[PDB]
Image: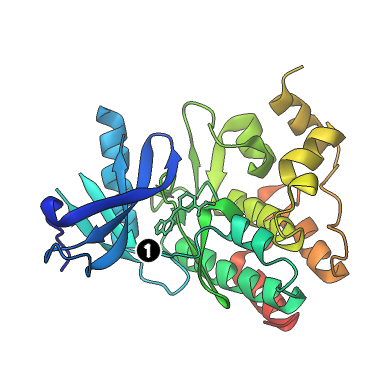
Amino acid sequence: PTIFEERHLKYISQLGKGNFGSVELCRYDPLGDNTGALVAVKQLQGPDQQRDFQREIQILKALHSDFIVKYRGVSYLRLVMEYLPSGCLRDFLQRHRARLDASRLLLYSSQICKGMEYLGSRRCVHRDLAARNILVESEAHVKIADFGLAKLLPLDKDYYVVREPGQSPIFWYAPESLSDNIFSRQSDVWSFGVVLYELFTYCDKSCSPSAEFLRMMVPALSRLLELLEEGQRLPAPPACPAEVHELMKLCWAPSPQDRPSFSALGPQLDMLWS
Ligand SMILES: *CCC(=O)N1CCC[C@@H](Nc2ncnc3[nH]ccc23)C1
């Protein structure tokens, strides 16, 4: 049930790639007759990376929420998760933009905020919150995924300092992450603000965090950190409700201690409805 025999995991396709592993679509088919259930299987494509992967597995196994991708088990080596055929929220928002209204965007925002609130209560920093890392379960249900960069906060420290700088697109990182590699539940809040912006632009590539920050934009990271320190922010998405934009601005407070908490954002997102 929680142990998946390797010989019964039948390879179908690649669901994703992202340093230093792959997510594959597999069918767990012990009968070998193509009637078994579909599963998403993560594996490393390294000694420290192996320690990193086993930590990811321990983090995800211990998470139990409707807004967090379900852990199924392991195969001995590989992490088995539930398969969400709708895939990432980024690509989903692009294919269904003429269908999802403000209410719907607000429902996804609420569900993600509930998921982050729960991660925070687990002393877990996600570090990579973005629409491409969030999965769609159904039309009215999103779940947070990709815990490959997630960190557990020690009981006496509310932040974590990363040794080597990030390998993710710089446009989701908080100023303190860009300058000092400081990651905390508050830097996750900053990233959540960028997710709100992604939602309200339906992840449109022309006004995307990368496209729009680059045109507002010496190394690029230092230049982005300069824009941000001056108080420059991403513009309100086209037709964005003022209140949603005011929330993104709060998430984007310069000092981590001034950003609203996930528990304060939730009732506010729910009040705007869905
Ligand atoms: C945006 C493309 C996309 O759908 N992605 C990014 C690559 C990894 C994919 N992960 C994934 N897809 C389906 N079901 C999953 N369960 C766990 C991880 C899963 C998402």
From this view, report whether residue 189 is shown above or below residue 229: below
| Left or right, residue 240 beside residue 190 | right
Crowding near pointer 1: few (<14 within 10 Å), some, many (20+)?
Answer: many
Secondary structure of the residue carrying tag 1 is loop
Amino acid type of the residue tagged 1 in the rendering: Tyr
The picture places residue 126, in percent across and down from the top left corner, at 49, 51
Q: Is residue 110 left or right of residue 162?
A: right
| Badge 1 residue CB within 8 Å of ligand 1 | yes
Residue 229, can we see it?
A: no
User: What residue lies at 70% left-to-right and 55% top-to-bottom?
Assistant: 203
- Which quadrant is the C terminus positioned in? bottom right
Image quarter of the N terminus: bottom left
Residue sitting at x 26%, y 60%: 27
* Vertical order, 89 against 142 (above or below): above
Residue picked out by circle 1: 83
**Looking at the picture, how far across and down is residue 246, in whole percent?**
83, 63
Quarter holding ligand 1? bottom left
Percent position of residue 146, x then y: 44, 51
* Residue 122, placed above or below residue 228: below
Nearer-the-camera pick, 112 or 37: 37
